[PDB]
Image (cartoon, helix red, strand yellow):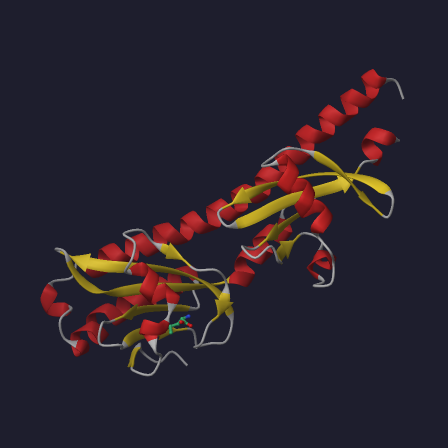
Length: 247
Ligand SMILES: CC(C)C[C@H](N)C(=O)O
């Protein structure tokens, strides 16, 4: 292959694969920002209630509860809730259409979504974890809600992590996402989810090359091409065979 031609093929495929990597990055970004906007809107609607509606538990149930429910329905969230400093949490949960209940048994001050919300003025986004209420893996968005400077409680919104997984999987390209512990999280090719697959070659090549920088690596003595980039605490990657440049 004339070097001119090989370079043309390499430049083309780098552009192609870069573009697809960016689509997967965008998917992750847009998922987060939609959920943040939602959480912010809910914060605002709660905080705009008069204090009278907020300062007794029965009023929280009757005035906040409907808001949690409507918001939960509007986005098909798994759980939407407001945790109070007395350790109770007003919980709107998926599934029997019973009204939101004020639960005293959920150990909320032990939870990262609660604690961490009180240490930042931003929305806090958890890693994926197993929700204690409905026993599904969720990503939680939490926010300490204040009215005229006084804490009301900590809002939480649980979105199934499978929702993000499914969005990533639908994207074009052989793209995939690792979580903060560098464990595979999502992939267009579901086979990459096998927990016994070794991802060191890709992850090592990423470590050397940095975000969005295309690299070459080997699999079973054949050349492949790829790139990764950080997206929040996740690492998004794309790989392909190098046959496009070599053959
Ligand atoms: C209402 C909260 C206790 C729910 C949250 N998903 C957790 O498991 O901590």
